[PDB]
Length: 128
Image (cartoon, rainbow, N blue to C red):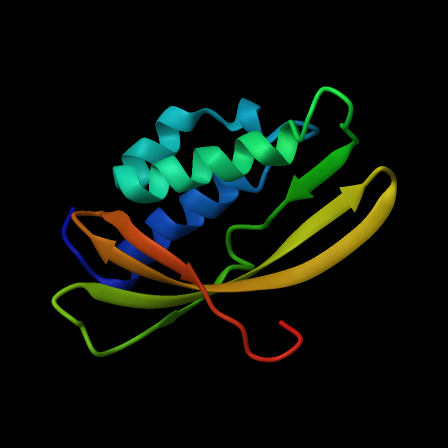
């Protein structure tokens, strides 16, 4: 409705909750939703990660389970406001790869503009 940290949160939360919540194919999450939560640039990169994630080649596919809790998404409001709104985002992605567990926490900074994500960029602290 306007912009605020928590308004920004919800957009990021939905972005992540949508994209990192599927059963086997990340394609089923509805690419329209990301288009609403994020700009074309972040939309286009995302759909591309989705594509290669699901389909590496006709000779390679495997079960991938990804799921994330929206309020387990730690969004550290980054204050600077570089004309845009910088929000540091860190969220664990509960994955299972062909029955094998993988649980890691991705951290990316997300920039919010126009009630959307206008840019996201992966960051790293150390191991993650």
